[PDB]
Amino acid sequence: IEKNFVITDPRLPDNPIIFASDGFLELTEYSREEILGRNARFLQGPETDQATVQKIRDAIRDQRETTVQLINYTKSGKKFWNLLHLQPVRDQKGELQYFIGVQLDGSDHV
Ligand SMILES: Cc1cc2nc3c(=O)[nH]c(=O)nc-3n(C[C@H](O)[C@H](O)[C@H](O)COP(=O)(O)O)c2cc1C
Image 1 (cartoon, rainbow, N blue to C red):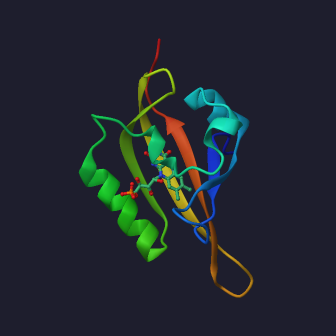
Image 2 (cartoon, rainbow, N blue to C red):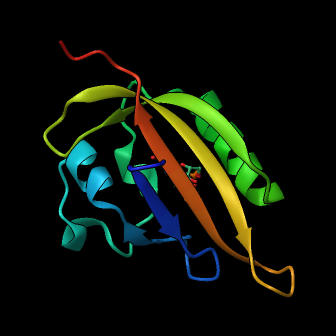
C-alpha cells in the first residue's frame, strides 16, 4: 500500500539511505543520485521542530517503531507536513538490519 519510502542501513556510517522509491523521488523532487548514501535529515529546514527531530533520534536509538509529523522541504524549497512512520527491520538472527521510513504529505496543495 505504501508508495513513498526509503530504506536506510544503520550498519553504515550515519544511517544512509540505500533505497528510495519513485514516489519518494517525486514527493521530494530529488534524483536517486542526489540522495543515495545520505542521511534523510536533508529534508529538514528552518521551521522543522527540533523537539520532533529529537523524538525521531530517540526511536532510532531504541530501535522502535514511531510516527511523527514535521515540516520538511522539497529540493526546490517547498514546505510540506510529512507524516513520517519509521519501522526497524531485523534480520533472521534478530539483529537490526534496516529502517524503513514511509513519508505521507498531509498538506493539501490545491
Ligand atoms: C528510514 C528513515 C527515514 C527517515 N525519513 C525522514 C524524513 O522523511 N524526513 C525527516 O525529516 N527525517 C527523516 N529521518 C530522520 C533523520 O534521518 C534523522 O534520523 C533525524 O534527523 C534524527 O537524527 P539527527 O538528530 O542526527 O538529525 C528518517 C530516518 C530513517 C531511519
